[PDB]
Image (spheres, coloured by chain):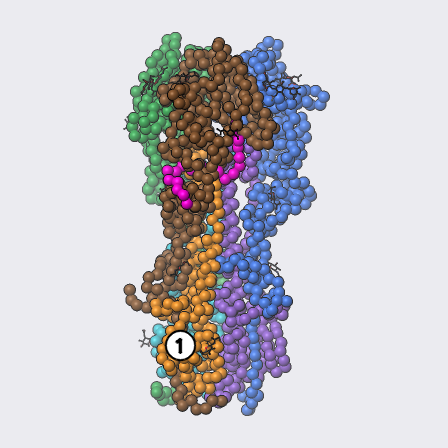
Chain colours: A blue, B brown, C green, D orange, E cyan, F purple
Amino acid sequence: QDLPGNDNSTATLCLGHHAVPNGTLVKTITDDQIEVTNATELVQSSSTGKICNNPHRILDGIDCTLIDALLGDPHCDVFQNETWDLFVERSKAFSNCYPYDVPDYASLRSLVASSGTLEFITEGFTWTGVTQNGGSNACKRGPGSGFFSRLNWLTKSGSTYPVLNVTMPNNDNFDKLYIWGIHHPSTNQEQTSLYVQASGRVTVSTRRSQQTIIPNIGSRPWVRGLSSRISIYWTIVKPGDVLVINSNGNLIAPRGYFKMRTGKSSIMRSDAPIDTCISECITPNGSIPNDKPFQNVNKITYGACPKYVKQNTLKLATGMRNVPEKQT
Amino acid sequence: QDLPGNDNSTATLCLGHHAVPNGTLVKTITDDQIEVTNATELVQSSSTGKICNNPHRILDGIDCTLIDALLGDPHCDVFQNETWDLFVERSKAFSNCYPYDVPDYASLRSLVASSGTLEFITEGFTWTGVTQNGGSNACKRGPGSGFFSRLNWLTKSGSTYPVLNVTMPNNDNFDKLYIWGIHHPSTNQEQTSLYVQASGRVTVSTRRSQQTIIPNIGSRPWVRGLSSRISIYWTIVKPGDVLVINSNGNLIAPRGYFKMRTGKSSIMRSDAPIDTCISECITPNGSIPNDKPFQNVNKITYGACPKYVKQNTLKLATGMRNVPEKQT
Amino acid sequence: QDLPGNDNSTATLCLGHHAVPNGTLVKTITDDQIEVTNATELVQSSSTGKICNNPHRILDGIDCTLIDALLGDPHCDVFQNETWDLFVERSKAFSNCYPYDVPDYASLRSLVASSGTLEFITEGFTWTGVTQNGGSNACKRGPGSGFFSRLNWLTKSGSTYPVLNVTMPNNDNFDKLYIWGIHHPSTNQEQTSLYVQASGRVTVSTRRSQQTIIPNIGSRPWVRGLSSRISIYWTIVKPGDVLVINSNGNLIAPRGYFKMRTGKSSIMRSDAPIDTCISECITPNGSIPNDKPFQNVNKITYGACPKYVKQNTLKLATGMRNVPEKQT
Amino acid sequence: GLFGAIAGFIENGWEGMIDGWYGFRHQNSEGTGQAADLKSTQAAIDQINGKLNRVIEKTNEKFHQIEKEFSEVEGRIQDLEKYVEDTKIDLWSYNAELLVALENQHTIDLTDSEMNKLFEKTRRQLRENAEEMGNGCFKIYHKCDNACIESIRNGTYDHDVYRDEALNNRFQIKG
Amino acid sequence: GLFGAIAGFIENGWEGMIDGWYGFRHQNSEGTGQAADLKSTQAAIDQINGKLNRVIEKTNEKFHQIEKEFSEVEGRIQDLEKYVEDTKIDLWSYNAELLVALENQHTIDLTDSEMNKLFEKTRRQLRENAEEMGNGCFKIYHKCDNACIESIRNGTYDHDVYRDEALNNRFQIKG
Amino acid sequence: GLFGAIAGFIENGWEGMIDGWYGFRHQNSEGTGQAADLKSTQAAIDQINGKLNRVIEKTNEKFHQIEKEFSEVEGRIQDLEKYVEDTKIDLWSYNAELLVALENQHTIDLTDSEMNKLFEKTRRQLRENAEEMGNGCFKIYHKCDNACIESIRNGTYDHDVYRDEALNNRFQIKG
Ligand SMILES: *[C@@H]1O[C@H](CO)[C@@H](O[C@@H]2O[C@H](CO)[C@@H](O[C@@H]3O[C@H](CO)[C@@H](O)[C@H](O)[C@@H]3O)[C@H](O)[C@H]2NC(C)=O)[C@H](O)[C@H]1NC(C)=O
Ligand SMILES: *[C@@H]1O[C@H](CO)[C@@H](O[C@@H]2O[C@H](CO)[C@@H](O[C@@H]3O[C@H](CO)[C@@H](O)[C@H](O)[C@@H]3O)[C@H](O)[C@H]2NC(C)=O)[C@H](O)[C@H]1NC(C)=O
Ligand SMILES: *[C@@H]1O[C@H](CO)[C@@H](O[C@@H]2O[C@H](CO)[C@@H](O[C@@H]3O[C@H](CO)[C@@H](O)[C@H](O)[C@@H]3O)[C@H](O)[C@H]2NC(C)=O)[C@H](O)[C@H]1NC(C)=O
Ligand SMILES: CO[C@]1(C(=O)O)C[C@H](OC(C)=O)[C@@H](NC(C)=O)[C@H]([C@H](O)[C@H](O)CO)O1
Ligand SMILES: CO[C@]1(C(=O)O)C[C@H](OC(C)=O)[C@@H](NC(C)=O)[C@H]([C@H](O)[C@H](O)CO)O1
Ligand SMILES: CO[C@]1(C(=O)O)C[C@H](OC(C)=O)[C@@H](NC(C)=O)[C@H]([C@H](O)[C@H](O)CO)O1
Ligand SMILES: *[C@@H]1O[C@H](CO)[C@@H](O)[C@H](O)[C@H]1NC(C)=O
Ligand SMILES: *[C@@H]1O[C@H](CO)[C@@H](O)[C@H](O)[C@H]1NC(C)=O
Ligand SMILES: *[C@@H]1O[C@H](CO)[C@@H](O)[C@H](O)[C@H]1NC(C)=O
Ligand SMILES: *[C@@H]1O[C@H](CO)[C@@H](O)[C@H](O)[C@H]1NC(C)=O
Ligand SMILES: *[C@@H]1O[C@H](CO)[C@@H](O)[C@H](O)[C@H]1NC(C)=O
Ligand SMILES: *[C@@H]1O[C@H](CO)[C@@H](O)[C@H](O)[C@H]1NC(C)=O
Ligand SMILES: *[C@@H]1O[C@H](CO)[C@@H](O)[C@H](O)[C@H]1NC(C)=O
Ligand SMILES: *[C@@H]1O[C@H](CO)[C@@H](O)[C@H](O)[C@H]1NC(C)=O
Ligand SMILES: *[C@@H]1O[C@H](CO)[C@@H](O)[C@H](O)[C@H]1NC(C)=O
Ligand SMILES: *[C@@H]1O[C@H](CO)[C@@H](O)[C@H](O)[C@H]1NC(C)=O
Ligand SMILES: *[C@@H]1O[C@H](CO)[C@@H](O)[C@H](O)[C@H]1NC(C)=O
Ligand SMILES: *[C@@H]1O[C@H](CO)[C@@H](O)[C@H](O)[C@H]1NC(C)=O
């Protein structure tokens, strides 16, 4: 080997690991505060406060709710034929035309909201024997009286309101959404003055369904100078089917159809400002980054968003236990 | 160093762990019966059999359902202006006044149940031209005829029932719940005898909504001597809004409003006895202790309760594997 | 002690583990592709394409939907008093009798579907003063006119339709399901021709409930030669209760009751072929084996089935890490 | 379990040890004796309690909810009410079952670990003076009276004090 | 994995071993051979089967439920029907994905453990007669024929029989 | 944690080590030095990143859903809407909480393991030439200059080169 390898010394080698002066507390199966070298947060808890207008198509409703934009309140005429990935409805929106109510407002708002288009096609309905285009001063269009742009108020002609019985075939290859309605007079006098018959009736049907609504006379609260109301209804006509509208008074008639589509559109109530930036995840509190798996900003989301959780912090340890060498 | 250790002997040291004669079987990732030194049960599976009357305010309905207590069945007059964290409804409860039905009984029962108060304010409705305070012998109050304490049955005066058109503004800063109704005569004779018009009509509305209900004449089964029925309806009027009640016959009118609130109240169907003890968790089978994380007593709970699970036992090992030394 | 005698040598012993040339990639907490010696699939992803007719009782609807089979469309007379664990409805099914609509079609289809029997008991209703057994040419039974086998169309006798007021007690110890209906004329002339009164009315009630439906005159689309429609309704009568049917025109009367039961029956829309084999799990795509815990064939299942998951493969490692000698 | 001490290289537990979960049994110049080790007993206990406490952490409270028992047959809506609750119950039942399975699995490896950690610790301390008999017992190769055994248990044993005695005994012998 | 034997101090598996999952390879003055170890092979297999069985334990059965495919547009109620089911599917999908992740993670550490437990067991048995070469091979310092190798594998090896031979060979040498 | 090296037989971490997570400090002929070990540092880092990546794997996207904030009191249907969402939130909250708990628990045992694996690896390499002082330090019983220390760290140390020097120093002495 060598010869008498005599140098009798020894050495010491010690294994160890790092430690940091700072260090973060994380939860465990056995402990709920244990300090680790490093951790990363998994709950996103803050919004930018602004709805980024990209990548999705945000339509700002300004002072229109989607239903008034659909019906055609004069002040919402801006929205005709408009489209959206997300329609934002503002707390300030207001109606300002004839007083109406929609029996299942929630379904009609949902149904239009996810269709995502207000594309309207006018059809040639021929109303014979009634006066068309009735309006009201509660729905001023310009200096004059008006009404919902997409609805046609029919009243008597001369001394008679005939039994209207019209039909419109769905000959296209898509579903047609028809919004129609009925007028509820305040007084029997009002009823006979407008529709002659002392009791109106609207029956709208297809091969698949039928709705017959009869009006209801009586005073409601004064809203924009009026105690009358009109209630809104909707009928979807499938390809190949046929619409038959039959009325003997009080019909607020459709002027055509909205076309329906199938996509990712939705609606959101939010007063957040829209801004120019790209963000996938929208929250009514403004966009949030979807880098983290969970979020605690809002349970209402649209887009690729983190999963809403009750917790506002959850730290994933990304380092060993911190056992400091003093702590400095 | 030291000198001759004449004797040079050895020693034996053995490390080990305890074991118990008894020992419990627990489930694992790899085994489903493995015996451990000790375990603790995580599924609570027994009730005391009694609803502790503390900490929540239990109201025992005795022989009143919440809806009869709300309407004011004579025998439930005990409950006027009462309040509850939990209203217990008993299987024995019975109605004993005019036969009625509530079109969405389930919503009205829910709606009142979580409001948690039967606080009633009487308002000055002025009914002109009709006879007020109608009653019936099926709703005996004392020796005489009666009706629901919170409802006012209007019939004609002399030879006429006028068109009632009244209004009551919500000027307070809270929502008002109005319960009203309509009478369905058995015969057309009964209709004209009471309400003169051969067809009644009730329209109750606010700025936001309207309900027009028309009665339905016909014989129903004899219930407490009667084939007639009254159907109950409800209208909430928001602050600043206004109620308008308009009828031309068959109106069962409100005497004021119940005030609504927002809290933790609910309703429970249970025949368990109430007792004096404190328990946070209530089950229709009686209170249960919420020390364990899971429970298997009932899926219906009120209060701080364990999570209902299908399992009736789940043992968490709180000790090592039991490897005893004797045979079996 | 032991005496070596002569040899002086050493030996080498090496511990190791197997490895396979092939080997499967599995996901982990720390890796998402790590190769193991062996794995097993936990997501069932393929159907046989056929509904095995065993162990459950599959009833093939052929060209009848359950509601037409219930009402008694002539072409569905095959199904009278039939029973099922699963009623399969086919995409090809068609109605071919009087045009009808069912206001809550979805509930009636559910309600019958889980009852699982079409057992019909005919009861002795006595209709005095009306013509019974009305039929139509849109519901041909044989060469002649007909109508739903389980319904009885009443029209005037001579010059009068009386007020029908009949009753049928539930004296048995089970619930009785009564399917009844109302006829909606196309024209007022049609109304008076058939039911004399210009406005019909049907009130069907028990001690617990009442439904009063009034008909609606008007033209609907021509369906099998007709613009009229009949709407179908249902009433369950509990043991001890009593049915009272009261009408003054337009009643389509029940001929008896379907008896209800409580079991595991359901309905499924599927065009899969039924075949003879035993399979516990049914999917509208055909039966699938329930050996695996999760499945990805369809979210619609009947029977003992694996839990539907979005994933189409999930491999459970059943072997160690594969660290081969050469490569993989 | 994972470390193979409990029900592993240590053949069985001692029903006799009542004063702690892990411990020592010796034989030495002064007779025989047993003693629990309280540091590892506490380590094992503290972990198991921590684990236990985390599982009993807050029952969340719920007040008005949906109806869950119905007396009439209603159809579409009541079917959803029943389906929302039944899928909620199977999901929480899954959770409970997987939770105690993972937990128990870990509690057995945790206590197996503490057993093995005490074994290793004792090993390290005895240095060249003892040999492992492979059943959890060390053969100490020097005269070790009760105070010597006490210092190994309370962790103050100085191997140097006995190393030449031990090494002579352990190796030299006759080969 | 956690114990660092498989794909750790043991370089790679043996594609050659077909008769069991863990085993031995030796070279002695009489020849060379290989042999599976069936006790650890079975231990690893039994745990993995147990685990496997618990996962295939009961498909629960369900009969009438809610509709899940609709042909008309209805609004509020049908939106809830669709939402109840989609949140049910994402929750079960989460469970499946987390379950095989935890499981696989554990199956690798379990088999790594068995590998290391067999290594330790063999270590303990050879006592002062062998040294660890650090790659899972022991250098046995005494003449060990095939019967000697068989006794190490079947666990009956008596170290005392060879200790003086071994210690002389192992230490003495020339330093 | 399970292996008992970190906050175990290794008393505390070194705030001084900035160039890696695990490492060596020595004291020798030419002095006292320190050095991170990059293979174990990377092993620990790669596992923790893999784990981290799996958790940030796809936010799934959702578009039209149910309403979750209401302004009127409606009864039965709105109660279900609220109940579907609240039971969805408590279930996802449960999942998040249990996920980071299992994860963290494992990240501590994983890094404890790597610490212990490096300790074992160094042990195996030094063979008969060093003794464990029981606090993570080996006492090397032969003259080991800085190149000697660097070969132990870079894993090329040949024990045979020093074995007679070491064994003489380590045993012989005077007993
Ligand atoms: C039925 O009863 C209701 C409630 O009493 C009557 O409603 C009230 O009718 C008056 C007269 O039209 C309304 O007056 C107008 O109010 C506006 C705003 O203050 C003001 O600009 C006009 O100068 C006028 O005062 C009043 O607002 C309205 N109140 C409500 C709550 O609707 C209704 O007229 C009665 N109808 C019949 C036919 O008896
Ligand atoms: C319409 O048809 C129904 C059912 O046939 C008739 O109902 C029945 O009417 C009679 C006479 O009022 C009721 O009699 C009562 O019986 C009780 C004992 O149960 C007795 O205490 C009373 O003094 C009285 O006699 C009978 O209960 C009732 N049955 C049902 C099921 O309601 C109804 O009278 C008919 N109405 C008309 C206008 O034709
Ligand atoms: C009310 O308006 C509707 C729609 O215009 C009318 O419906 C149509 O009525 C005609 C005459 O009965 C139907 O014609 C028949 O069609 C069948 C199939 O082609 C054929 O066999 C007959 O010879 C005849 O042509 C037509 O199909 C029907 N169309 C629709 C969509 O229903 C209805 O007649 C009007 N009613 C009144 C009272 O004015
Ligand atoms: C109160 O006066 C108005 C109004 O609403 O402003 C005038 C209006 O006609 C003009 C000049 O625009 C008239 N429209 C028609 C079609 O008759 C309505 C209608 O009679 C009531 O609204 C019925 O409820 O009443
Ligand atoms: C059958 O006799 C009674 C009754 O119910 O007891 C008498 C009752 O008046 C008395 C004396 O209390 C009367 N009430 C009124 C307001 O007319 C009612 C009512 O006519 C029917 O209930 C209509 O359906 O009928
Ligand atoms: C169009 O002609 C028919 C028909 O449906 O075929 C003839 C039918 O009677 C014969 C001969 O079967 C008749 N049934 C009755 C009970 O009157 C109906 C009925 O009047 C309408 O359907 C009302 O809507 O009309
Ligand atoms: C802490 O962990 C996160 C995620 O692994 C990482 O981005 C960050 O750099 C770490 N901190 C340090 C100081 O390494
Ligand atoms: C809406 O779009 C349709 C389809 O192209 C078109 O015919 C119609 O005139 C449009 N109207 C408006 C106001 O844009
Ligand atoms: C988000 O918005 C809701 C409702 O507007 C509010 O209660 C919540 O605290 C907000 N959170 C954040 C992080 O903005
Ligand atoms: C068993 O475990 C439970 C919970 O840790 C504890 O209360 C009980 O005292 C234990 N049993 C014994 C005998 O230690
Ligand atoms: C109910 O409470 C209101 C409000 O204080 C009170 O005015 C009313 O008279 C009370 N009536 C009864 C029966 O307590
Ligand atoms: C609780 O009550 C329900 C219904 O009353 C019953 O089926 C259940 O078995 C009871 N369980 C216990 C533990 O009381
Ligand atoms: C792979 O694992 C499955 C389940 O344990 C088993 O059936 C199969 O035989 C295994 N493959 C081999 C080659 O052992
Ligand atoms: C249906 O079953 C009932 C009950 O046994 C029987 O009376 C009736 O006649 C049956 N009808 C047919 C067509 O099977
Ligand atoms: C099952 O059927 C559905 C609808 O018919 C289809 O989209 C799906 O891909 C099918 N899957 C299999 C495995 O057959
Ligand atoms: C350890 O044991 C020895 C012998 O009993 C005693 O002198 C010494 O002080 C003990 N040390 C501690 C810390 O108990
Ligand atoms: C172990 O191996 C030896 C040599 O083959 C043999 O004599 C002995 O009986 C074996 N023992 C067992 C239990 O197989
Ligand atoms: C290890 O260290 C020695 C001394 O510095 C050096 O000669 C040798 O080449 C190193 N080997 C490697 C692979 O770094």
Residue count near mark 1 (Cα–Cα under 10 Å), binned few <14, some 14–19, many ≥20: many
Instruction: Report the front residue among A282 and B231.
Output: B231
Instruction: Report the front residue among B97 and E114.
Output: B97
Q: What stretch is highlighted in magenta?
A: B257-277
User: Residue F81 at x, y = what percent?
Assistant: 51, 38
- Disc 1: which residue: B13
User: Residue F25 at x, y = what percent?
Assistant: 59, 75
User: Residue E60 at x, y = what percent?
Assistant: 38, 46
Instruction: Report the front residue among C185 and B253.
Output: B253
Residue at left 48%, top 21%?
B152
Task: Count up the numbered dots.
Answer: 1
Depicted F32 relative to depicted A246: above or below: below
- Could one spot residue B234 in this view of the protein? yes
Please give the chain letter of the residue carrying mark 1: B
Residue at left 49%, top 89%?
B1
Q: Is mark 1 on a helix, strand or loop?
A: strand
Magenta residue check for B175: no
Depicted B199 relative to depicted E156: above or below: above
Residue at left 47%, top 70%?
E10
Residue at left 61%, top 83%?
F29
User: Residue B47 at x, y = what percent?
Assistant: 37, 46
